[PDB]
Length: 307
Ligand SMILES: CC(=O)N[C@H]1[C@H]([C@@H](O)[C@@H](O)CNC(=O)c2ccc(-c3ccccc3)cc2)O[C@@](Cc2cn(C[C@H](O)Cn3c([N+](=O)[O-])cnc3C)nn2)(C(=O)O)C[C@@H]1O
Ligand SMILES: *[C@@H]1O[C@H](CO)[C@@H](O[C@@H]2O[C@H](CO)[C@@H](O[C@@H]3O[C@H](CO)[C@@H](O)[C@H](O)[C@@H]3O)[C@H](O)[C@H]2NC(C)=O)[C@H](O)[C@H]1NC(C)=O
Image 1 (tube, helix red, strand yellow):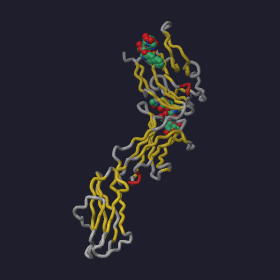
Image 2: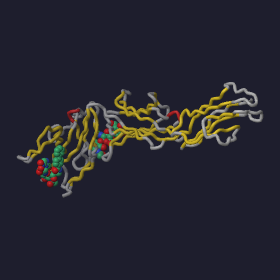
Image 3: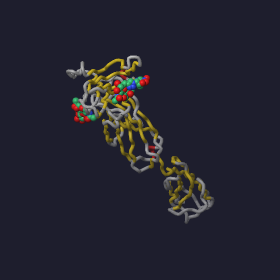
């Protein structure tokens, strides 16, 4: 009994004040249409074996001459298209819509769910699983809404400030999926680790509607800071010098630590402190530590000993 076959999304989302555009097609194997009624939450009376409830559209009354001012409009034909449109949609419209249709001696009822919330629902940011420094990533912000009579826009904010990188916004309004996607590419620095990325929903005039925030987990090599005593780095032979190596940032945590004298690894220096108890003249160069993690080896600044 596959007499009727409808192609449309199973659920359409919107909010109070906006509009909703419902794509819909059908194929009636039993000729063209004779009547089309649009119920809101129809209740089937088991006694009379008919459908009751508030009728939002009747093809025999408010659809005999299309009014163009109608809030609820049927944009379809007699045997193919059942695209509905409520502009503006209200909270009292949220529910289950019924597409009661009749042809020659047979009739059919079709359900469409219309979820309308009082406030604009937030979008959603889809992050890559591993974000690493100097590697371009594509952040995806999706929104399960798109209507013609109410244009929207998605805005990317980093740390509460718009991002200079351009985005690409695309909308799909088909019988399969309805959404507004905005993708943004940018090469993250190590400092972006722990920073907040926001995707804001705004109308045509740019008024804030909703948003979704995330915190970046940017892998990076250990950024190091080196200290030396004395600060002036001046000494005589035999006297002591101490250098310290402090990991200021590393994602993930560090693994090994070694020291370098003009690019030469001093052996047995597996700690963050470099003690030169009795110095000479042949030393006196440029020192730096190397701390690594899963990401790789990170190097600190250079200090001129010069003795
Ligand atoms: C080709 C054909 O044969 N077409 C049938 C047609 C169904 O095939 C067709 O409409 C399929 N779609 C549904 O069924 C349907 C049901 C509910 C909803 C919906 C939508 C929005 C909100 C709430 C609901 C949308 C679709 O059905 C009838 C009557 C008919 C009467 N019943 C009673 C039966 O007990 C099951 N039932 C009960 N109940 O409590 O049992 C409560 N409501 C029902 C249907 N079951 N069919 C009709 O005239 O529409 C005859 C017609 O010739
Ligand atoms: C069922 O029939 C209706 C009526 O034609 C179809 O609706 C029409 O669809 C087109 C494209 O989908 C709409 O064009 C759009 O216009 C806006 C401006 O309002 C523009 O910004 C878009 O880029 C696009 O050009 C059109 O407005 C819309 N309505 C009417 C009255 O024409 C509907 O597509 C049909 N259903 C299916 C599943 O095809």
